[PDB]
Amino acid sequence: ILDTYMVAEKITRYYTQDLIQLSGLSESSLTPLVILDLACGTGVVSDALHDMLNFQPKGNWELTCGDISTELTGHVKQKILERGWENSIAKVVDAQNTELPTGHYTHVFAALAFTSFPDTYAAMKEVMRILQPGGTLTISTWQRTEWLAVVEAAVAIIPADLPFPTTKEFMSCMNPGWDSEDYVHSRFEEAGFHSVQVTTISKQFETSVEDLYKIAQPVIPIIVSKWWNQEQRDKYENDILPALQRHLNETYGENGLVPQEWTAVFATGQKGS
Ligand SMILES: Nc1ncnc2c1ncn2[C@@H]1O[C@H](CSCC[C@H](N)C(=O)O)[C@@H](O)[C@H]1O
Image (tube, rainbow, N blue to C red):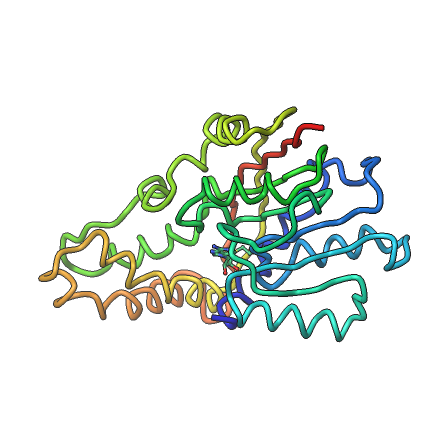
């Protein structure tokens, strides 16, 4: 689990500054700040919060870093000790059942996580419960990644007529709609948030062929489970990663850098006073 997430955090860190800006955190009048990094992964939002809030003492604001994964939580637990984040606690938190206190947080952040929750309605209700009156929820969700297009190119050089999902189909297998501004906006209002703002932001970067291969590796079995039949899996499932190796090496080289543009929906809203 953790090795894959160390590859992924090189990318998700590019989306944290806009999340924090959209939240209004810098201008917030709520004090002291009491912040949750929900589904924190390796903690990239927490990294950015400690950079922004490094003009102030540790006692003047509080941070909880919560994730369902014990392995990812342990990584953040160690980062807290290493870097001296004395105001911060990392612990296992299920977004659908947080066990966190009612009316506690001034700000909840959930970066690139809501589509992973089997019951997003339970998670939205939990966030509304654990926010203070006047508290803020700010989230990001993927609209378009481009690692998938590299796997599609690999399947295309397997010499058989094989199905492969588009960006849209892959996004919509679990929790469709969070790639749409209007859907996300409506979800915030339906959950009880006010002063909802939604926007869409792209980042342009480069990813190594080695990193693209590691991103794709755990998702290949899911892809062929959902979109291939058993005959197709029997004959060709083990051909995908070799084809991806070949595609990446021949197109970009063993240490090539693959241009990337990924786009996310950002949304924020406020609990009533
Ligand atoms: N029910 C749940 N409750 C809390 N975290 C969950 C969850 N289901 C999945 N997750 C976590 O959601 C994360 C999505 S990856 C996003 C991680 C991080 N916020 C970043 O921007 O890089 C993973 O760390 C995964 O373990």
